[PDB]
Image 1 (spheres, rainbow over the protein chains, first blue to last red):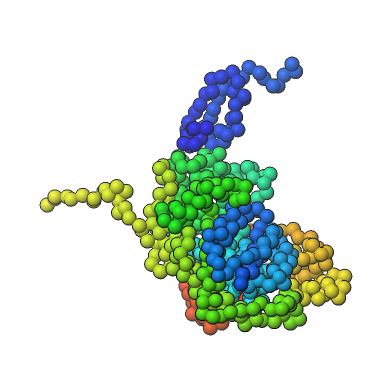
Image 2 (cartoon, rainbow over the protein chains, first blue to last red; image 1 turned 30 degrees about the vertical axis):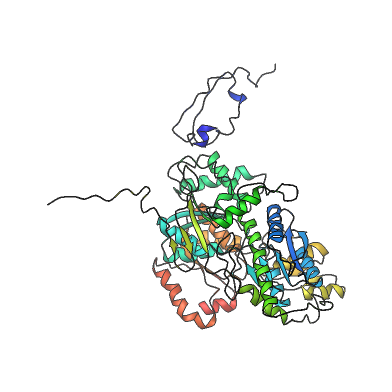
Length: 49
Length: 391
Length: 147
């Protein structure tokens, strides 16, 4: 929220949310703008189990 | 005797109806009582405005306060031009010379034409909502020719509330192509918070962009969100809180409970509501001038019907409109003075600017002078060009 | 408003008639409520309105397609106010997508005694750019004044 409110989610910045729950927080807010985030996921929803 | 008036209020103008009844209880005098008959409707329905204005014209009123839209300004300025009933309103100033309509919301046309000169803009977008005339857009395309401007206007008020996020993200990507680093947002509050949410969510509030929220209520929406980042917004303010008449009001306004005055327990008033307090000051001064110079008037025995065949004039309305135009009160907006048409003359509109500390007034605009800089020759009296001791 | 109620009081089945840019909200709100299905040759309304039947078809689709036909990117647009600004909103939104250089000018607020003075001030501002493609969106009496 703070790198949005100061406007550091434009192109050029790059992030890594080094959690195992990349899609557990609100990444819809930073989803546009140009800041290429990355992450790590253990619960892959493309599975039968 | 008490004085019967009419109130045309929307179903959703909460703070304005509070600031109507605040001016009712404060400006009241034992000589005469400005007792209203309040009707609620939407101003997007000419069927409703007609059925209300005829019901008020039937129920013996001597003036009517109310709001209007694009959808009802022509219902009003034909009715009050016809039945000679004067009308006092805070809505957008009509494009014409209409009789029996008193505009409390001044103008920003030459003021917005003044500000663009002050930044020396030449190439800039212009997002507009329909919502109130289009008379700003016509004025800034008239002047865009002879001042060498490249306006890219976009109608933005057609957007429904479910395809909101998709279109604005589609919208600024177009202006991103043309390297549009300047916008104007000729909107109202409920839209200009949505557009500053979307230029945040796509990250166009960095350094380089420049904005103008061309409302008279610059500090009525949430500018805390865009307050950082580098996008130097600007605006226009009529309710300058650095004043004695305002700060005394903000005392008793902030103390009102939001049960008998809903949306009043706050420290900032909307400029729609602030003029609603200002307009009751205007009637009560003019209706005092009615009984002062011995112009004592009766309504009728029946007041007829609005759709009479023919619907007749009444000469005592000629006195009331002329009384409402001679008003020299001082209100929340400042100097309330009208010309012979009901529009504001000799008024002051404060050019703001948003800085990291907050809203920071760096000028004012008046009808007579110009866009006038108030003080601060240089930001902290700096820059002093230099003295070069050369040969 | 007054003549609408007299015909509803006389019991009409439907109403033919004209409206302007001013009385358009007066008609379309009445017939949308009282179901007095309104037939008109006046200009089509901005949006959807029930019980209004609009015999003047449109102009926007052909006025855009004619512009792309002549390969246009730089031109003027002289408009009157009286039919609304529905057409002006169309070619100004499309100027964003297609990189046109519209130079729209309001001209319909000019009265008879200030015609020749301001019309010279009108076409002077064209010579600041030397624009030679003009769209004269007016009506018959006004387009004769321009031609």
